[PDB]
Figure 1: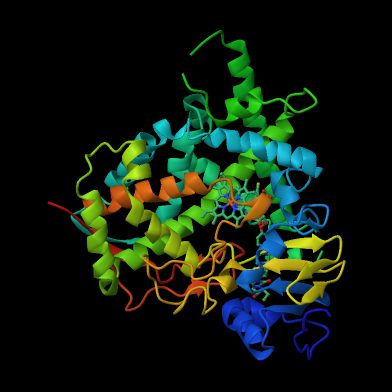
Figure 2 (figure 1 turned 135 degrees about the vertical axis):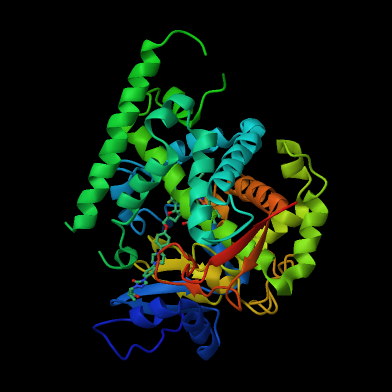
Amino acid sequence: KTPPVYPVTVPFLGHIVQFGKNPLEFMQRCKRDLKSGVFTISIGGQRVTIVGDPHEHSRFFSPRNEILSPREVYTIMTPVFGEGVAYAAPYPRMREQLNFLAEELTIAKFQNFVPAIQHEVRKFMAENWKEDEGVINLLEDCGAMIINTACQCLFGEDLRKRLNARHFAQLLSKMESSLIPAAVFMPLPLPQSARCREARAELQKILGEIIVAREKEEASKNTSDLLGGLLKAVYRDGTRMSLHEVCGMIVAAMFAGQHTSTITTSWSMLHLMHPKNKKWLDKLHKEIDEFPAQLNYDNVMDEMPFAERCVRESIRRDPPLLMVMRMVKAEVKVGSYVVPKGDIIACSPLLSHHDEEAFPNPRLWDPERDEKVDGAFIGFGAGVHKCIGQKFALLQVKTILATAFREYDFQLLRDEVPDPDYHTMVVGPTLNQCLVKYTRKK
Ligand SMILES: CC[C@@H]([C@H](C)O)n1ncn(-c2ccc(N3CCN(c4ccc(OC[C@@H]5CC[C@@](Cn6cncn6)(c6ccc(F)cc6F)O5)cc4)CC3)cc2)c1=O
Ligand code: HEM
């Protein structure tokens, strides 16, 4: 009564290679050949069970940690975030920590993000896109805007002086590269590891200097930044976060937002600039050609409904995180099947977002589409572990789109839209394809 396995033919290596080259075509094949949305594969002799039937998402996102656990599956992050941070911490602390973070997105806070976001976007553009026309690599530039823009929202002035975006990005890169996606399924002292520690330590040292400089300061002077937020925070037992933990959280917050948003921004701009999608590009300008130079939280939140769809449909068609997993601590029901204890249960936004019923014509970028199966869209996950940076990411991306398409027009050099590059653990467009020509207006 367990879900149908997929033929192996190579015990030394599971479906690893097939999945790595193209996991969409591969997964759809499985789900197609076995006549079942729920199926099990073997990655290096380890049963990975995939809930690929959107109707059955709740069976994956609903179970509590005691039954379904991410900790063992997400071990690989521990080196990046810290030896005692989320997924490296007992869930009670983990959850506890993640909440502090969430309280940093009170949207009591967004009040000042729009002006900041636009301040960095306009600056970058007026710094890199000067000429009346020119060629840039969209993916690399959005990455710059993302990090730059994110720091201008969460990092205080004093911190940004010591740690600027350009520099912070290098640190993330240094440690995030330490990551081998394969490990997640298959549990070293590589040059990548070393760089990762130093980078986080460096970041550590600095954050230590700033705090010291803040605590010596007295006694007022207005809205505290992310770090300050984390520093104030106190546990359920009544103890303040250790810096090592505090650092980890910041890495986490920044790490998680860097690629997912960078990619989402890119895909969005790509589709939107494509001549085939003139329909929606126009519909977009129709929505932003009314806004003033200085945008405010209100109009980005409440006055850009079609732009949100653009971002959502981007994440829908090409989800940055193609799947999420958990260790099955106890046998869990799923459809007519049963997932045995020991399995790595996983749910794939990539797969689900391409189910014919939930999203007819999956490969078609349609911003006005809606899930034909409730719960089908899981770009930001769901249940207890539903993404926390959603509201922020969306705000961050939407505002960028508004500032970019307002002052520049774009043109995709390549005939069609970039192919997804499935080799990175966070998935976006290839970037050997992202070459774009911009044209300043007036
Ligand atoms: C073929 C051999 C080789 C050759 C080259 O082909 N090859 N080629 C290609 N692949 C290959 C490629 C990819 C993969 N992976 C397997 C690992 N998967 C994976 C996905 C997500 C993941 O995330 C862990 C948590 C998820 C939530 C999040 C991130 N987050 C949330 N919001 C913002 N960020 C998070 C949450 C809370 C938080 F607080 C912080 C957080 F970060 O981190 C962990 C792992 C991805 C696919 C495997 C192999 C190869 O092996
Ligand atoms: C498009 C942008 C983002 C996407 C697509 C995204 C996607 C996700 C997904 C799919 C998950 C579920 C992970 C899992 O189920 O295993 C998740 C969780 C999470 N993400 Fe995001 N996320 C995004 C942005 C962010 C940002 C900006 C942050 C930080 C501010 C962030 C922080 C988190 C956190 C804290 C969780 C909770 C993980 C947990 O509770 O265990 N995410 N995100």
